[PDB]
Amino acid sequence: KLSLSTKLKQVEDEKNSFREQLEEEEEAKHNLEKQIATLHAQVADMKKK
Amino acid sequence: KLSLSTKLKQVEDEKNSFREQLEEEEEAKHNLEKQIATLHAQVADMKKK
Amino acid sequence: KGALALEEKRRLEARIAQLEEELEEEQGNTELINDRLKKANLQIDQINT
Amino acid sequence: KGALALEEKRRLEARIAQLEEELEEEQGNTELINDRLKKANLQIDQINT
Amino acid sequence: IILEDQNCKLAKEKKLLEDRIAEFTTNLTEEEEKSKSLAKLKNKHEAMI
Amino acid sequence: IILEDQNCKLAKEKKLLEDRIAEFTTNLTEEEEKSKSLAKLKNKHEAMI
């Protein structure tokens, strides 16, 4: 029980860490995707300009 | 123990499945960063041009 | 085979135990016959004197 | 562990053989002691008469 | 998954049961001989009486 | 089915050992009851002998 509880808690902490890390990575792509749209729009606008 | 054993393997799948998303999220961020670098470089290149 | 192996000891246990009573017969004879000799030797010695 | 019962049962068989061997050895010893009782008993009936 | 926890539990119980059986079965051999030996002991007094 | 087959055959061991341990423990105590019962009855012969 302690080994399973400790292992379950350890796996839960690892999974919980991935959730917080996933949020940083999930939101990181949003800022990167928004920059691509802004950079591509500026590149297209600068190219046309 | 049945609930802990089942939850232990269940949490492992979540930590493993979520971990796979980190690689895809990280890889997606690298791909967006690569495009951002080219787009940002094009902006500076188009701006200087 | 495992269940029969453990049960096999019970068969020999009863035989090894029942055999103890048979061996005790000869063992008791060494104590009963010898004890009778003491009572007989005491009377034989008194009768001889 | 189940096979140990056969080994233990087989080991007990050695003691069973010793019980039978001791019976034969005790039978001869008991018979020898019985011979002295017969001679002593006869003296109690012969010397008394 | 449920069978793994049940099979693992039965594995530890089966191992402890066999180990505890030897602790009690071993005493049965001494008690069997002592109990059977005591039976013939009572007959010795009857025969001697 | 393969996992259940092992658990099925292994479950019988835990059930057989649990059921045999109860009989083995009672068997060892049976000699004590017979020995104690015969010893008590044998005491009467000792006092009479």
Image (cartoon, coloured by chain):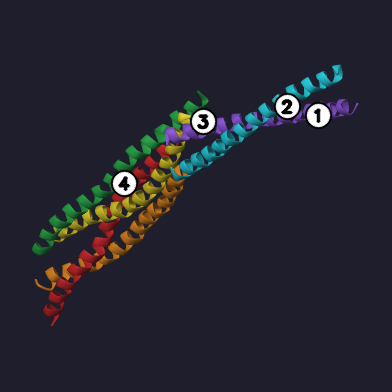
Chain colours: A cyan, B purple, C red, D orange, E yellow, F green
Q: Separation of disc 2 and disc 3 at Cα?
A: 37 Å
Disc 3: which residue: B10
- Residue appearing at x 74%, y 23% in the figure: A38
Say above or below: D37 vs E14.
below
Q: Which element carries disc 3, helix, strand or loop? A: helix
> Gap between marks 2 and 4, in whole Å?
90 Å
Direction top: furthest residue:
A48
Mark 1 nearby-residue class (10 Å; few <14, some 14–19, many ≥20)? many
As shown in the figure, which amino acid type bears the numbered disc 2?
Gln
| Residue linked to disc 2 | A35
- Report how far apart the C-alphas of labels 1 and 2 lie in the structure: 9 Å
- Taking the image as shown, residue E33 lies to the left or right of residue F38, namely right
Protein chain holding label 4: C
Name the quarter where the N terminus of chain C is drawn.
top left
* Residue at which label 1 appears: B40
In contact (CB < 8 Å): disc 2 and disc 4: no
The answer as to whether the residues below labels 3 and 1 share one chain is yes
> Are the residues flagged by discs 3 and 1 in contact, CB closer than 8 Å?
no
Q: Residue furthest bottom?
A: C49
Q: Which residue is at a point 63% across and 30% down the rendered structure image?
A: A27
Q: Is B17 placed above or below E10 here?
A: above
Q: Position of residue B6 (x, y in %)?
A: 47, 31
Three-letter amino acid code at disc 3? Gln
Q: Earlier in the sequence, mark 3 or mark 1?
A: 3
